[PDB]
Image (cartoon, rainbow, N blue to C red; front, top):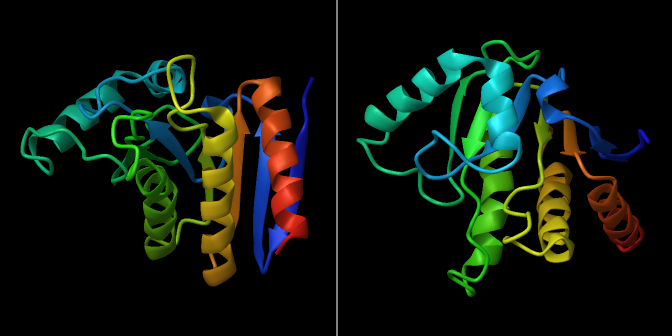
Length: 189
């Protein structure tokens, strides 16, 4: 059952939608990766499959050249082409491992969103879709992650002109959680 909602934040639009992020026609989609940039869970696989094999090659080059063979640190971002995807670019990020660094993980998760949005702003890209970063069966609790995600996006869109930001959720359950949290956040502006 397809569902979405939109709320304007100054001249920006924030949308939450049930959907397959690989099919988004926003200029940018976000891949929540492992630090190698070669894998990751859930959407990562689907993104690599849908983008084609040139993506993995572009990730390997980023790893070799810009990252000097190192993992992308948690909360940072890099950008590649989208290759076969209907989106033009992929911003790749690494979300924190839930309870690895309890006192830093809220900021680190926030960083994924804020660094992605800054890049979009600097590069004058006008639309971006995020997946649910770091969530999953062995991961960050959806209720707290959703709150950090929306809070961070709302605060950024209050202070910056960006355009359209989507949160694309494959799970109806997750969408409903984002919907409640968003209502709660918009009334208490």
